[PDB]
Amino acid sequence: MNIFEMLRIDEGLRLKIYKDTEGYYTIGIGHLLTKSPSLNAAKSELDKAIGRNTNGVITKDEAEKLFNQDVDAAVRGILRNAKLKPVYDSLDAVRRAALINMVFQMGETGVAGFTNSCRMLQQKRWDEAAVNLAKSRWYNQTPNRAKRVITTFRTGTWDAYKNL
Ligand SMILES: *SCC1=CC(C)(C)N(O)C1(C)C
């Protein structure tokens, strides 16, 4: 298991524009196109992202290319955030993947709260952090996924993704 396999499990793979859990146009492996209600706006974002006139459908290779860019972007976003970098640096590789997973799903920029959760992770109070992370819109809206990510933070193992 690694961050790519983990997110692939959590995000799925769809080659045609579809709506994510929040109702937003998305494609590939969790690649958010726009929060705009306009499908045309979403298709324009897609064409720009891929570099060709697609009309809503991409190939698996193209989906994996956006995925590589998105994971890279989540990692660089973490390292450029003065608040997240110290937490990421304090974690082992498995928990670092859990943090990348959260950033991939909700972004670094524009994310409200979680200051206390991050403080508990940096303190390595795994059980307390796990409880705290669950008191969130994030957990309530996508509980099965949040549970897997939280279990990863609580245990530092891939148990939530094995046999899954
Ligand atoms: S460690 C929890 C956390 C803090 C903040 C910077 C708000 N984030 O985006 C996540 C959800 C990673």
Image (cartoon, rainbow, N blue to C red):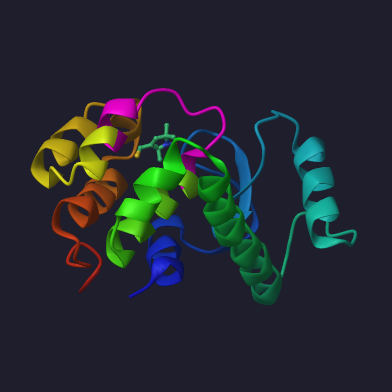
Task: Locate residue 82 relative to residue 102 in the image: left or right.
Answer: right
| Residue 51 picture location, percent across and down | 87, 61
Give me the residue at 63% from left, 54% from top. 27
Give me the residue at 60% from left, 48% from top. 18
Nearer the observer, 118 or 53: 118
Give me the residue at 30% from left, 36% from top. 118
Location of the C terminus (image quadrant)? bottom left
Q: Was residue 61 drawn as part of the magenta stretch in this picture?
A: no
Residue at the extreme left of the image, as rendered: 127
Query: How many callouts does the rendering have?
Result: 0
Give me the residue at 51% from left, 47% from top. 78
Report ligand 1 position as a quadrant. Answer: top left
| Residue 136 picture location, percent across and down | 29, 27
| Residue 50 picture location, percent across and down | 80, 61
> Start and end of the magenta stretch?
105-118
Task: Locate residue 44 relative to residue 61 in the image: left or right.
Answer: right
| Residue 109 picture location, percent across and down | 57, 33
Asked if 18 appears above or below 61 in the picture, the reply is: above
Nearer the observer, 145 or 16: 145
Residue at the extreme top of the image, as rendered: 112
Nearer the observer, 116 or 13: 116
Nearer the observer, 80 or 27: 80
Task: Locate residue 92 relative to residue 159 in the image: left or right.
Answer: right
The answer to whether residue 28 shows anywhere in this view is no
Picture quarter containing residue 49?
bottom right
Task: Locate residue 115 relative to residue 155 in the image: left or right.
Answer: right
Picture quarter containing residue 9?
bottom left
Location of the N terminus (image quadrant)? bottom left
The answer to whether residue 15 shows anywhere in this view is yes
